Image (cartoon, rainbow over all chains, first blue to last red):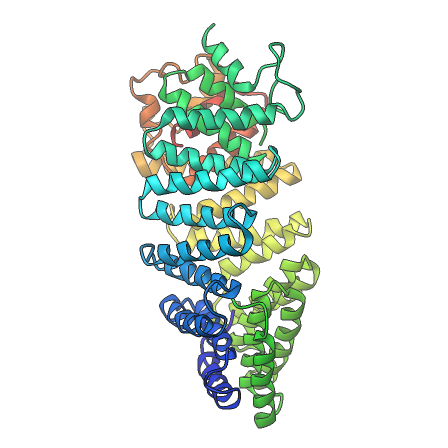
Length: 250
Length: 269
């Protein structure tokens, strides 16, 4: 988006000018390093981009101090850049610290914390640290499900995410229950209090195995995923029920 | 990716400093404006970013010439900005102009031209002009199917996009053929020559519709390991193609054939 030619050296002038005018100490030096970091990211120079954010990080820690919101953003951005190079180990602590700042500022249960927890879950997943992924998605789900309505997309999205983590660990039961929660709640979004005369799709699926309700891209995924668990259990007719529901709502 | 405050003033100073030195019509001024455009884009300020990139474009046309590859790069960037605000109407001319240059410099049948053609189609698709979309994708597909191999990803991807365009027009037959090409090629890449004992999945599918076979993937057809053999074809694109074609069978009321491809896709999941 910015042709690789004169941009970097032009910024390096702007920096030397800022250092001479605003003082060597000035907080704005951090912002200039930030613009430099941005230019490097645009040229896909990720290693170079990360190096400069670090320098801006140190300046913001001195000026704006620890626990300052702008330090939290920096730590996230640097964690992202580290992730793009596959350096997940060194990204985790940066991300874990940002979470601690965010908890101090907003409180343990603000929606923006649940964002960090999901970001933090995703990094661990890239390191194969399943037990921690489990932990972080559970923390996030706790916030989403409590703070927001049952119909909120973050709930189902986190539940799917956690389900996959459960699958990785061989916790098939826990995943299956999660999937059923999503479908049951979606069934109850127009078909009332799910009485005997009114069962959710997965019940019909399983009762069909011992021998209409297809009225969202997230639900679709849930349907196909629970379908895969039935396939693992050898309940192929139950699997088709959910699968045919998905492929008809596309 | 950059602190919400004070970034813009700092760039504008860097700009005015260059402006003071070398007028407004210097390539360095253009680049600095582009950096400023990049800053605005980081703050989701597309209106503000596109405004400046226009300014940079004007300088780059005057200084570098109206056919310079940097001019071509800017035109794309500026179009991306317009598309992001949903101003697709004003994006098209710039994208067209970028294509004209690309062809002039690289040659009509360069892979990068096909990429540029693909973007032109997507822009037309945002305007609901199916006949333009059709033409651009066909042009693109032509560059991919020729200059690249038979199982190069862009071929499968471009075919799907063109098939999607056909569907919207009601060209159900033309869509279907494309899917069958994708599956047949995928089948031949895995199994070589088609041997009659080596028919593609969709053939078997339509044969099951013929033979009135409601027995699904609960039992294998003719061959013991048939379901695990026909699933050696594994791609996110193939699966998409499998389902899209299944949807076409459903439109024709061929429910059994639809299931065959859909159940095949379930097993690849």
